[PDB]
Length: 214
Length: 214
Image (cartoon, rainbow over all chains, first blue to last red; front, side, top):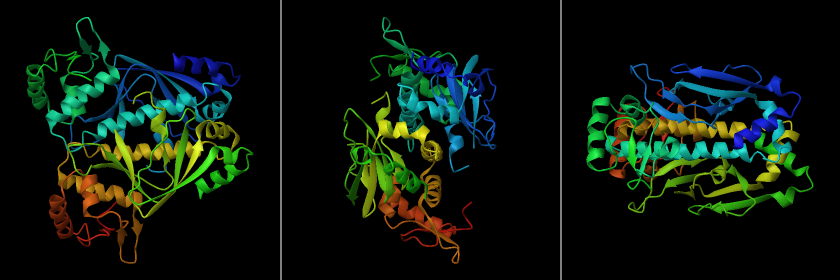
């Protein structure tokens, strides 16, 4: 609703097509930021990706965090520091590439006043903090926290059945990568979670007992 | 140098004292954001604080991340989500409280064009990612990564002696809290790190062998 108003705001300005560009991707494609001189901000309007911890010792990398619809991307490119890569997890994903100077100019002007950008950032921060809570935890503790973080991020409520359901692309292998553990271990932990009535079934898409969750 | 130019930019506008306010703190004071209607952004100009993971089961909380000079604070308050607290670690700390609407208006206008705000955010993100690398690691692996993260953040080079030296407030207890482990364990790990020539001495302030580091 809110990025829609923003996109609509963007189109009012004569330099819109010059500064705002769309890109669509499919499963397993990598999203890559061109290190042009004039840099841009990226908004995901639909679909999901994963940011991976690059470790060439590992065949499949862990996933550090997911990228959700309405996230801002490429802020990292402004950082004074200098590896992670970004893979599309859903069947498709669409984003907008917006020239950053442009966007940085129309903040003051537009009475959805930058709140939109600050709020988007604020939410990524909050998700970063939630993840930091995983430090020093056992794999079992991590899987609860993961499935909760995802239910908050990306889950869709049944309620009639008193369940929060996760997207299809969150399977055993992906869950393991996000929990930074192995698949055989995730499998065993998923059994425990069903015994403890956290999870309705061991099988994806994961259905999480609404009760058990906040 | 750069927040100085910004502060100087701020003073040009007639509404400066109305929107920009200074606050000084001492060791162990808590920095608390008033949840006023009109919200503000906070810039640290000198000193250090720690953000703590609140766990009432624990006598001393772990430290999730440090707050450095030139960090922006209070962006979390814009987030659509809803615990951590913030403690001054150095003898003193000074910050500026800046009304966010004001600040959000003078971005376009000022030819240090918002780059400053984006860059500040970008750097906090980069430090968040570095921390996420601590997930699923042993305490020994964490202490290396911690001492490296801090050397990058807050360390000051000798070079003549080929050492990077950390601030005085990083002692054994603090290191342990940041590594999310116990003190007796940190002590033992510090011995290993001296044997491995990572650390020049087991004693704070920590001096890190320039070689051993990137």
